[PDB]
Image 1: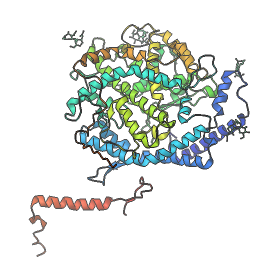
Image 2 (image 1 turned 90 degrees about the vertical axis):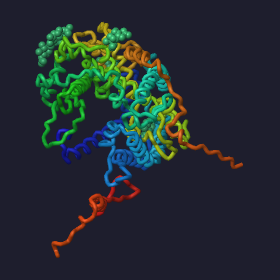
Image 3 (image 1 turned 60 degrees about the vertical axis):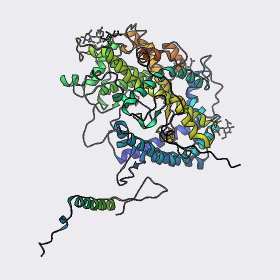
Image 4 (image 1 turned 30 degrees about the vertical axis):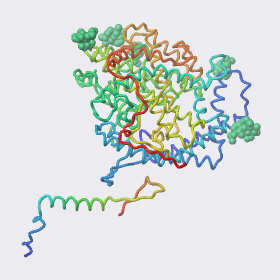
Length: 576
Length: 48
Ligand SMILES: *[C@@H]1O[C@H](CO)[C@@H](O[C@@H]2O[C@H](CO)[C@@H](O)[C@H](O)[C@H]2NC(C)=O)[C@H](O)[C@H]1NC(C)=O
Ligand SMILES: *[C@@H]1O[C@H](CO)[C@@H](O[C@@H]2O[C@H](CO)[C@@H](O)[C@H](O)[C@H]2NC(C)=O)[C@H](O)[C@H]1NC(C)=O
Ligand SMILES: *[C@@H]1O[C@H](CO)[C@@H](O[C@@H]2O[C@H](CO)[C@@H](O)[C@H](O)[C@H]2NC(C)=O)[C@H](O)[C@H]1NC(C)=O
Ligand SMILES: *[C@@H]1O[C@H](CO)[C@@H](O[C@@H]2O[C@H](CO)[C@@H](O)[C@H](O)[C@H]2NC(C)=O)[C@H](O)[C@H]1NC(C)=O
Ligand SMILES: *[C@@H]1O[C@H](CO)[C@@H](O)[C@H](O)[C@H]1NC(C)=O
């Protein structure tokens, strides 16, 4: 279907998916009569547990169809929402095209404010009752499955039991998250202060030097990433960053050389060759013909000895990095190729994405570019280029940590009933002021529903995977080239001509889900929990640079200023 | 007589462009107006 869009392909989807789901349900019902606390062999007990879930079928039929209808309605309203200019209501814009481009390119305060306010006011108002009832349905469903709430069901992903002291209680996750965020707060404070100081020049008379930042100036709809502010926060614009886009042009690099170069890099690292069958039954480059196919990169796990990658080639570095990312996914896929079907997966949700990130990062270093030959040896990069690159990386990495933590904390606290239904939005914004340090431009009462505007929230998805993986990557960094005796800066780490790092990686790759992720961490990193020290060590030079640059500044913020307090009027009424 | 009509050009140039813009606006808004059901405000219907 991805290769060929036909109605026959769509009905083949429907039939195959229905058959697979029916087979899974019938197998679960047949195996449910096997008791659990009798098999001491863990590698089969894990399969029994992974096949034992009764899912939403415990819930009533009418309630089940109502829930499915509500989910479909939420997805449809998110996908087809539209707002537009009051001045000329005859032209209207969706969210994915234009509006995202507007918020990622526009420099007008009024335009950004209007778009940010209008999208929420015209989507969240519709979405509010649906979520208010969906949370109740999910809570009932979770309680029907011996869980405290749906948040407990989500947290059960990391839960490990009966492995003689390596167990991890579900409640322990919260403690780890808060302890990690405590050490992250000081660096985020400095970064936020520097960003506010830099934005003071772009939007004068709109930002208080000690207040929080207005929400509609973050470069994104919600602020999940701060990359779009790079042009407005460049430390040294006189010298450009590391760009080699003309290097492949000079050598006339077609859209085939990328994969061969990736294979050569893998061979130099120590990993074996690649399957010719994979080269044949794959989609290295988009045909470009009249047949539509999605250009979104994705690795496939067909099994049986064949894999493939779907991504539209192009002569640019990002394509090289994405190829490395997907190739890492594919390597991890063959890593558990000799495992049962129940074990043909990663240790948890944050394992597949952690491998591709480190793989791309190892090849993204300028040292690798110099070694390849594209970057001539005589050319050199000073400290300012490194600072610019580190700031660019930080604007993507650090920015999402407080946002992700705050979102997950809000969802967890709302799923356990600790927040009264009539006191959701207020509490939400309070966290935004005190965790993230962002203040809304206009007050929002309880009729709105702001987090429901995000795709992950309105589609029943867990957001914690973006947090822990972000840590694991950097932790993997300490396990990646420190064993490979790398002595230079951590941002210059590379593992070419290092077979020990490859062996250490393979030792955990060739495990699948057969062993707990804690066991893999102890096997490679040597710990039994996620650590934040590697991340702090990675950004030490930029941390020192910020500390030097923040002497004439006020690190931190006060959660009382607002862009509307200067023109507001207070009222006081005493009826009695 | 059929060729003698001085036409609407006798008006001032700014007034002429204002009239032309307004007529075009009327035509466009009539051609592209749309209303739809509050029950499902995601699908909306034209006139023709
Ligand atoms: C748990 O049971 C499985 C299922 O038999 C065992 O896995 C097999 O082990 C035998 C030898 O004991 C091998 O010949 C098979 O290749 C293994 N694969 C299968 C069939 O799953 C496993 O050994 C048992 N756990 C123990 C006893 O350590
Ligand atoms: C989910 O699976 C469990 C398996 O135990 C089912 O619970 C059993 O329900 C049957 C009757 O349906 C009883 O005879 C057993 O005593 C129950 N065992 C218990 C309490 O664990 C449960 O009904 C299943 N739900 C559905 C509809 O799939
Ligand atoms: C780091 O970047 C700065 C950019 O100027 C340079 O270091 C400073 O350079 C100016 C003029 O040369 C002088 O103040 C000093 O040589 C440096 N300032 C210090 C040490 O405080 C240099 O290009 C790079 N390397 C170092 C060690 O600063
Ligand atoms: C270690 O591995 C690298 C990875 O490429 C190899 O570098 C080769 O040899 C020289 C540089 O040393 C280059 O001109 C070749 O193009 C590289 N090709 C090969 C054979 O991979 C080499 O094996 C070692 N060199 C180092 C230390 O980088
Ligand atoms: C397989 O790898 C070996 C060792 O790097 C190499 O000599 C050989 O040319 C490779 N063959 C393929 C299929 O690339």
